[PDB]
Image (cartoon, rainbow, N blue to C red):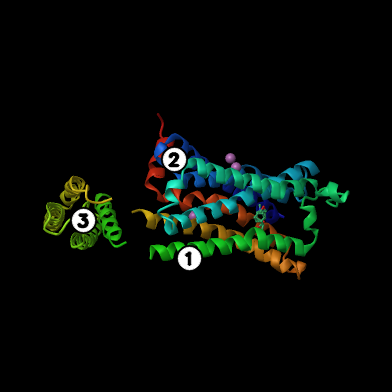
Amino acid sequence: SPYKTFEVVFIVLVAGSLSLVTIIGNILVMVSIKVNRHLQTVNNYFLFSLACADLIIGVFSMNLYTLYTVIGYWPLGPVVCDLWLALDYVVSNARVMNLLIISFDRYFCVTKPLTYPVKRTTKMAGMMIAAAWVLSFILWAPAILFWQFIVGVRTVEDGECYIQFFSNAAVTFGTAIAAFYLPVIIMTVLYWHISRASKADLEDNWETLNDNLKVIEKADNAAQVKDALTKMRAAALDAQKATPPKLEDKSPDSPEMKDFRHGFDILVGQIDDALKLANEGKVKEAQAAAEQLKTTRNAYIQKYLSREKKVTRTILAILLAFIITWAPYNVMVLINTFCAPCIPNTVWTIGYWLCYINSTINPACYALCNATFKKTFKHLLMCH
Ligand SMILES: C[N+]1(C)[C@@H]2C[C@@H](OC(=O)[C@H](CO)c3ccccc3)C[C@H]1[C@@H]1O[C@@H]12
Ligand SMILES: [Hg+2]
Ligand SMILES: [Hg+2]
Ligand SMILES: [Hg+2]
């Protein structure tokens, strides 16, 4: 049997690789926040706790589950089985309520801007996270570890490992409704109000100008400099015709409004001088003209202040990675209520692993898309 042996070797290598990636990715996130004060924001306190739960899944949950399935039975005894099940459900429950914290915290920043942001400190973020881990422990740990003593008998036979009060299929489904389906519904409606609040005009023109200015700096060919120069110049004219939040509410004839438009008139003059050199053949000099643009922009940035579009996109990615990876297991629980043979044990293992995969791809939802995390990752990996 040369094939059944290769499947075991393939599974061990794939499981060990996923566990290793989950460990490294989440440690890099947690260490980056600790060593860089620029990453010590309220949002990253919630991501630190999220990466903290993902690290426990990669270290304990993934490895103990791989040993369980490869050997074919539970070899570590009943005590370690209860501790593993309790740790798995508490850490998972803390993740779900962590996503609820991120969703509600973002909801009150767009619906209560005159009240909530001033109440949004790292001490409040630490208390909400601490309360989430305490509530998760109280909900799952005593029931998983001590239900056998309440009923007075341990029905989990030797070599088996499962939650004892889940012997009733309807009980498992009620758990799926309260611990997964209801939270996902809440996070979906919360995001629906987030994207509708994002869907005012001054932030859209200034963000387009700054984003296309970076594209010129890191452009590989001549098509990326032409598209960025035109789309930025279009956004610069729409940002010039509008009035910024100026002090004292000054008329268009004021020296503040005249010099504000004059700052954009200098920028368009340098943009067309960069567009010229890009067509003369000095595409490298047009990229050197972007530094002159960044100087003029910085010389007249005192009239303006938004990365909130990226923040909303980041939350959606974190929520979708949670829904997509945890949905297959929960529909198996639903089908299990009326047809247990409809879900083979191989399908159960796959659905259980997909939930673990949520911890693997979670850092890639935000860390590999944020400019500050990338710079800190490079610094953590270079040899001093
Ligand atoms: C570690 N898991 C893979 C186990 C199986 C799944 O369980 C669930 O999806 C249920 C809701 O049906 C759930 C339990 C606790 C917290 C959140 C969800 C995902 C997580 C959770 O700890 C268990
Ligand atoms: Hg941790
Ligand atoms: Hg933790
Ligand atoms: Hg992702």
Image position of 267 with respect to 28: above or below: below
Residue 192: mark: 1
For the residue with label 3, is its CB less than 8 Å from the closest atom of ligand 4?
no
Which residue position is annotated with label 3? 249
Q: Secondary structure at mark 2?
A: loop
For the residue with label 1, is its CB less than 8 Å from the closest atom of ligand 4?
no
Q: Amino acid at mark 3?
A: Asp
Left or right, 44 with respect to 254, comes to right
Quarter holding the N terminus is bottom right
Residue 62: mark: none
Residue 224 locus on image (x, y percent): 25, 58
- The residue lying toward the viewer, choosing from 134 and 327, is 134
Residue 375 seen in the current view: yes
Residue shown at the point (47%, 51%) measured from the top left: 364
Left or right, 208 with respect to 6, comes to left
Which callout, 2 or 1, points at the residue further toward the start of the chain? 2
Which callout, 2 or 3, points at the residue further toward the start of the chain? 2
Image position of 340 with respect to 271: above or below: below
- The residue lying toward the viewer, choosing from 160 and 301, is 301
Residue 243 locus on image (x, y percent): 21, 59
